[PDB]
Image 1 (cartoon, rainbow over the protein chains, first blue to last red):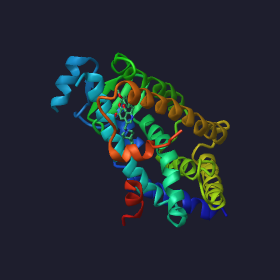
Image 2 (cartoon, chains in turn purple, red):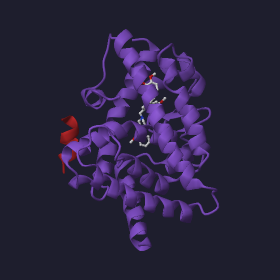
Image 3 (cartoon, rainbow over the protein chains, first blue to last red):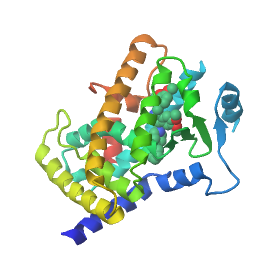
Length: 258
Length: 10
Ligand SMILES: COc1ccc(Cc2ncc(CN3CCC(c4ccccc4OC)CC3)c3cc(OC)c(OC)cc23)cc1OC
């Protein structure tokens, strides 16, 4: 019933606010100047970066920074997942599998909130690293960000807000087609409800947005490809750059992933 | 494992 679907929407929004300190609303505010004097420090070259770091090779320090921020993101996303109704009653191995295979799709969804066509907010909104600087990084590290910019730009053009994103991310986490799931059916029943909630949210929140639900679902597909490509790059780094490694939490996620 | 720990913390 539609009142239940709205209660679910609001619960997911409340839980998203409680799980994620940096919301798209706040990110977009920073990106567009609608906060205060504390305008972000712009990192557009190597001097910028040194100047900014104040308040190994450069590519590798950026890599290691993103991995550390990724650990905190996994933790917040896990906390969010535990607030999706039904999730904590799933077999615990299935919870692990949904997070293992879904967390990166969610990471890149939420990273898009921090992005525009020219760069990305870093250091919880205090800095802005330019697209051209990230692109300048040597191979393979210069290949990380660019397809995410390509994704973010088209994704942000749908103009989803935090309330929409909360249900979008829940739908993705509760995907019944992850490898190695023990009980697919209870996952699919939860997802089916989330999807109905998402459909109603998008109709009410974006009534004139043409085929917005369909376009959204399509994005969930595009995220999987973003992640496949990202994981292939991580593999290359592991094979050819082995002078370093991931955090243990990220190692768990990545073990036997694709 | 660390994932299990995150999932079961209250
Ligand atoms: C050169 O090497 C690399 C280059 C690029 C990358 C790509 C990349 N991956 C993950 C994160 C973590 N981030 C995800 C979004 C997340 C987030 C944002 C908003 C809300 C919630 C939320 O998480 C819960 C916050 C934490 C990044 C954060 C960045 O800036 C902050 C960033 O700036 C370019 C790039 C990031 C990985 C690399 O190596 C691995």
